[PDB]
Length: 148
Length: 98
Length: 49
Length: 99
Image (cartoon, each protein chain N blue to C red):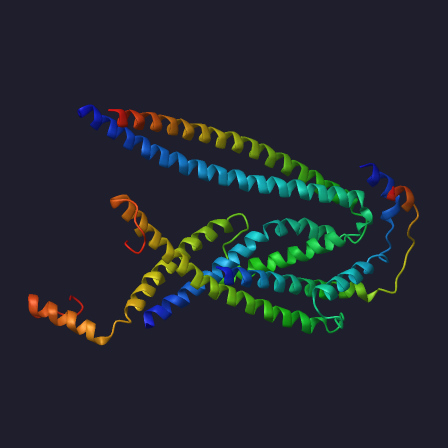
């Protein structure tokens, strides 16, 4: 019996280890996919430059488009520094504030979700609040509705 | 590389004269993409601002849908969490019995 | 979620159209000298092959 | 209700800010077009700058490739260790049933 107890502890241990390794593998695959996408984009861009140099008749149309995209990216960055009110901001570290405000939005959404449940159950008519209140009062004696 | 080398002399002297065609294709591409056959580079600014208005309206509607979507999916998530807690404590059971 | 997906599609299309209009605005200048012309198709054959 | 409309507006603020940051994340590459923007301003022969940019892209691509390879090896490592935990747990749990 004592041996079984030890086995149980061991299995709990391995459960926790499995949880952690599952997590780690998840982030590792996430990073792997991210770098896969990035390497793919880099090589595609390399190929585009190869075509541009080979097809120099391209006539900087792609260059014009990229310059316009650059201007638009600049404009978007300024707009975000405004909305987020983060003059201290760069493309490299904007990811950190993005995940930060993702957590922020998660907090806001979870709050408002609890709020939504409370408002939904607030549909209970006036009579229920009373009946509960006087029931509590009769059982304990006078108590405040907030404390009820 | 060999094509680049061969065309080197060909494309260098562009004379900024074959440049405006790119504007022509851009205008035509917009004409198909934007259901504005009358779209002219002159009146294209009114269309630009109007489509920007539509786009920002679309973003706003998207964000409202997103707010409700987020609250809803999170609510479903707590629903699921309650279900898992129930199954762990007791085992299989329907959500109605939960 | 279905509705929001549709809204996202519509938003993307609106953005693309807005960008095309921006492109027209930018290339109005290049349109300005549309009367210009230049030599072409000197070594096209071998380049094409 | 008043508090909830206020929280709703706060959620809206978070939504718009997150959306903007996402947009710039999308435009990450476009900021690399700063070279393209300067390259476009040449308005003359600029194949040399194109070749320089292509070489830089080649270096970046090779760096990304190595990064991907080493990340792949790391991920595989994590995979095998996780599988080993799986096997160990299976065996221990089997022995638990048997006992």
